[PDB]
Length: 269
Image (cartoon, rainbow, N blue to C red):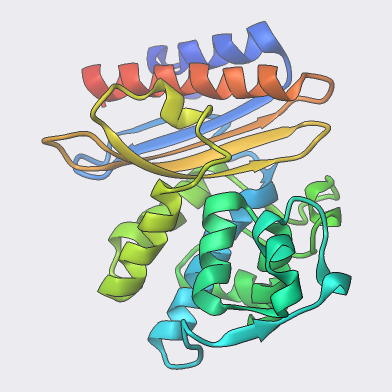
């Protein structure tokens, strides 16, 4: 389908054209293998979406005995950076458990929690190696926040298709133990910063779990595991790179893409 747009992609192209910027979408029905995409193989900054992969890397270390959920990771005020509500709240205690840090990155995108987890586990290179071992040769983690939220060639990027496939492996592919897999999905279900993105477009009664990411000046992302009653789950990733568009308007684009996803999933996909 290289000469003409597929009809199923037209609504996504129209959302992008009406708002400006560059919109990447990929969705997969895990039962049938049917897919929906727009710019699905283009690179976008992950921003906090990397934290959904980081949490899985840490839980895989728990599974292998290289880490313990209850181990205390020590830190001080010198470690705190912006958007770190949980680690900031606990700094006087001087430590948080691995389990609590994983929950903080998934539920609140806690920035310092993610840096502390990376400190425990080998840094961006080890996160990249973790996803490579899952068969993802695209996604790469290279820097720490805040600099990892700034475009710099291919550093700290994924594609919508690659991260959706990796999310499917992590959540449905038997790469984590039953307990770790459930703990990953639980944190993503309880996640707060993405509730006005893909999940706001889903029909009442669909269960979903997501991981968002944002930069102040351009990037608004979300990926989700979507569980409609009575059918196989779906994965959907939406990455929006829109310099000069307000954060609220960028979330509205993600909701529009989410609605296009629901229409696709309920009629052809």
